[PDB]
Length: 246
Length: 245
Ligand SMILES: [Mn+2]
Ligand SMILES: [Mn+2]
Ligand SMILES: [Mn+2]
Ligand SMILES: [Mn+2]
Ligand SMILES: [Mn+2]
Ligand SMILES: [Mn+2]
Ligand SMILES: [Mn+2]
Ligand SMILES: [Mn+2]
Image (cartoon, rainbow over all chains, first blue to last red; front, side):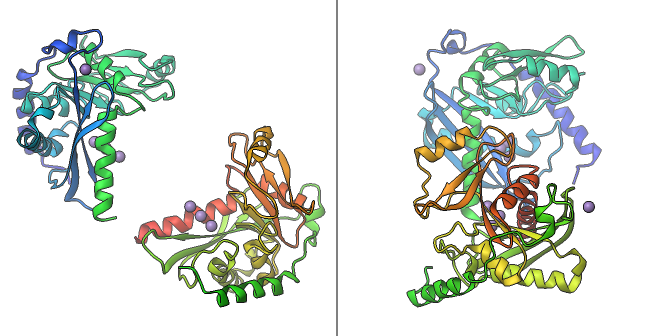
């Protein structure tokens, strides 16, 4: 199902041009506050699928109050997902539909626009430094955080024995270790998201946030391993699929 | 979905009629052997269901070598449900299909006939002392063991505070405590089947086996919490449904 190389080459070019717009520092007052005072609304996006369907998916956007993490907005919608999944090109599959949900939120409940969006996928921890979380952030201009559930093995990062030893060393929720690429760059952080979970999240900057702020906020959104905004978008979009054929 | 009383009466009557044929002692030479020397084939049966379907189910019979617990025979087939689930009458929902699978095995691989069958459900630990594991045992005349994953609250048995304290007292795989009826009789055993599980199994005699033999064999079949013959029939019958729906 993989697109031809000329197509991937065009997509690489687009990623490299948009990357110039990524802001990888704090631009919002709440981000420099020790307790995120001023942060009121946190967004989460995800896309679920039907096992049989190569065409149909369900895209969900949720907004949660902060710090209580209660759902104040949900839009789950069937969409005609086209492009296949190709590692490093996730945005070309999911991000056009996620942009449409943000625009629907602006049109329907503009006062509930999230101040930051947690994205199910990497940001700058990416083959070309421009993952789905950056891509969504640049297209919507919202602050975004990339949260991935396994390690993207790029710029020398490997899920080898040493990497797994560092995971064992993470002992409680909040513990972290930096992901340092062969380039000298800190690409992201491995984060132990709560006390009763050993498999880390991999957190990276999407847009308009610093890495250390992205980690700390992500930690604060974790009732469970998956940060509550992504988890609710994940749960609600699968439930929606289940309600309509299943 | 509940059947009329006349159907239930006929079912109670059928259970009381077959109960007279239950043999609750060891009748097989391997059963008195300290290591079950001579036991070579252990059977397992289960039926899986479709969430939407009131009609379609998938019944599975597996036979495993002993002591290696490798599957040497599998028969999984889709069937037409004829009766709904009513507690205390499980056999009238599932056991006609299991009997047919046993007869198909006799026709196809008679040398792989199991020497004992582990059944997903109670034996004599039952509202009328004749549960699905006895019912299968009498209809096929094979030795059967009842293995249930929850406690059937009958004859004064309750999943109360005292009961849950005794479960805490089970510390390792093989630990057990007896399930005593109000009459003082031992209906079955609670068994901790695995070191790395806390939730016990409830083991009772089906047919042609004693309780202590049934408990010890059940333990020896447990690679995980669920004894490997029932576990394999469960996995394979669910896989069949999943692939066809
Ligand atoms: Mn606040
Ligand atoms: Mn996702
Ligand atoms: Mn999933
Ligand atoms: Mn998901
Ligand atoms: Mn052998
Ligand atoms: Mn069953
Ligand atoms: Mn089940
Ligand atoms: Mn089952």
